[PDB]
Length: 439
Ligand SMILES: [Cu+2]
Ligand SMILES: [Cu+2]
Ligand SMILES: [Cu+2]
Ligand SMILES: [O-]
Image 1: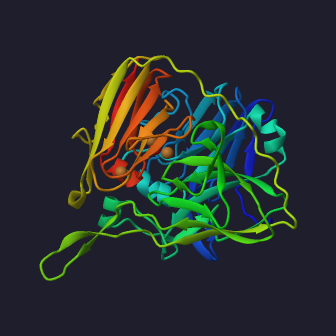
Image 2: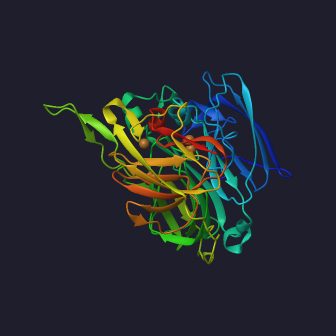
């Protein structure tokens, strides 16, 4: 096959993407070994669904797992009557998700389980895939002539040829694995044929962070989680927290081999030590550096000019309400809270009005990073930690380091009951989630 492994793509046909997937235990070859993973469509990652605005998606999920499951269409601004976080598909049963792709939408999205209490083990075991919304913007020469690839960043740990079980410490920290993979492959080689690459990046890990840096090169950020920036933004590195997506252009500067690395990053994970008094909690510190892939540049590379502009960001109405949400931890109990409470599916926490805009101030009073996610209603990050955000784009996950406040502009779109939660999915399973009702 191609030197660079990417998931199989399924495209809409005549404006319709009609597909049956089964969530199933699946024997595979993974990183040179044989293992049984939980997969959609018999692959890890699952197939990439590629659609255009106004397409109809009709996806029948058959549950062939021994436990209930469901889907979350992460990042899609569709109705929570479709993207229903409370729905349970029992073992052996099927459910059809049907929705229309919104008109004003572009970018990289993804699908994964969201059955409360069961997300972390199901996602860890391999249940994920990408969804790409194509854009008329993809036709501009500076993007059309770039070489495009999807990078699904997901780590894994295996024990006895199956995903490693969660330990108590894993429920506290979020589980990370020693196999740090791209598209389910261990350190693949990308032999570029063009001097400009357009990389769509997805962090589909439970808890691992990727502080991305390409040796000797900057990255040009052109999209965040849920849409394009207004113009490319040059960055030296790019942190991708769990659940986040980005698209970057890479302009290869000379012939050679360049490592794409996940550089050391301390997200505040904890360990335990006993030094004669003790036992107490002690910081794990930064992650060890990882090589993600080897990027080979072509001969005499002459990158395309960057796009001068991408997509203008919508002018939003003045906001009608300010919310303040506070995240806290009880680490030794592996319990996690929003405004002092754990999730209760019967309890509505926030009530808002459709087609109004809210300001959400999300404050991390814990010591760990927490990547905050809101379903259904993409937001504009205004500032984090008191620093203004350097671009305007739609996001649906925002990382908060210890002590930081994120200020979000949140237009409320579809009516109904939905959720917001930490996307370290162990923390969501352990209570860090709340309910928003839009009417
Ligand atoms: Cu998600
Ligand atoms: Cu968290
Ligand atoms: Cu969710
Ligand atoms: O989620």
